[PDB]
Length: 94
Length: 95
Length: 195
Length: 202
Image 1: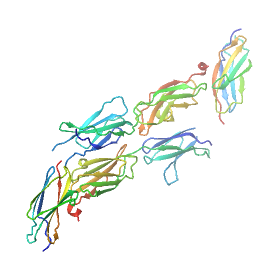
Image 2 (image 1 turned 90 degrees about the vertical axis):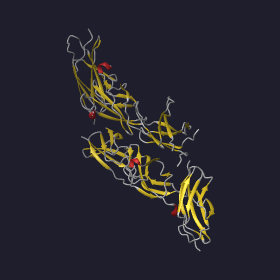
Image 3 (image 1 turned 180 degrees about the vertical axis):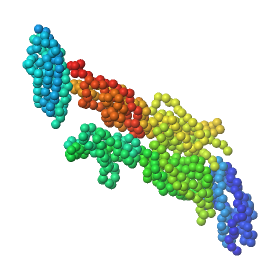
């Protein structure tokens, strides 16, 4: 019936070329969540965008450049619109 | 009859353009003196040369430049030749 | 009268220069900053054939003139002699220190400044101190040495949402001037940075 | 075959110090890379270097010759693998006050005008910079200190000076020292010159 909240927790575990995300749904269960929209890039979360299922808690980002400063966003969305995002900085291991 | 000696004493009293010399005959009276030969110039006593009577003790050098370093020589001579000279440095009095 | 000749001015220390000429007669010596607005002189009297003009600004070019006076009769001024005094360590600090985030690449800032006012010589190098900690003394900060010909520098791989401290100083052939006052720059957090 | 550091910069500090500074495009974020820095007089016979090791992105080369041009090169080494040397950066150190004294000071009477001599000398070996002026002291007295001699200031581009109105048959003393944009070198050793007397000269 309205836009969802921000996710409760977000963790990142950067690799040499991968970056692993682990999160948990919004603290308010009343609002419907259709899925999550992930964004990532270098110095900007607008570069790349994927949208995943509402039941996913883990995502593996692939084909990233080694030794770089990435910015990752995560938002939940439903039929109303998009919710306030959570941001996390992650650095790839050279 | 023989070459004379050098003069006994030589004194100079420089003016603004003149220089007055005063000397006395050799301390040895035996040797005959026919006269004296004076020389003067700047940095050299060969530039100008005058010869005077054996009985003169004073000579006045004229038309010299003010504030200059003149060199004066004095020798006694007779028919044998010229004797060893006396040298004296004299500086003209500036205007 | 005839003005003195062979006038030469030789710099001693960074505030002293010794004029020397060749000829009781009194000599008067005047000097003046050749590159200034004030067409006025400073002068002193002596009876020697030399005199030391003191209390001068360092790394500055001066002109010197001598005259001679005797029994109410003064000569004209002599030819001018030029002398440049020695250099000295800077007295001021670099000015207008500025830190701005580089767009559109966060975690990196561009530090910009302007040369010190009292350099007292040609600036050989700039020394830029910056740190993340509030307590460690200046000698344990991160040090970056920039050439005197540059007035900007790029710092990379900083941390996000963290207060940084900045200190900068100017060096010189004879030493290094004092540090500036600390500049506080707060890198932004991703929440604020994106809208 | 590793990548050599880039953006190598060498900036002269004092008259004996130069600060090299480079950047590496391979530094990540467990292993630390050692940088080797070499320097050498660019205009010399010895094609040999001096070097030092650090883990910082900068190093201060010290104990250098003043008013001299040096060339600097940096390499990086890690786990038995060395890179090639980076492009050379050139830096010339600043000037310093002279340490030696002027050599072969000579006094000769000018012909054919006595009471005047021409003083000739040669620039110092350890000038450590461009000589701005020579200071020539001379006196008639055996006892008065150096600060009461007759002082003559000659330009740094001239190696001769004329002194006039001296006295005849008198011992003169001569001292010379070189000054410079950064200070003044030590006085030379005394030169004894005896003006001739009119008797001997003619």
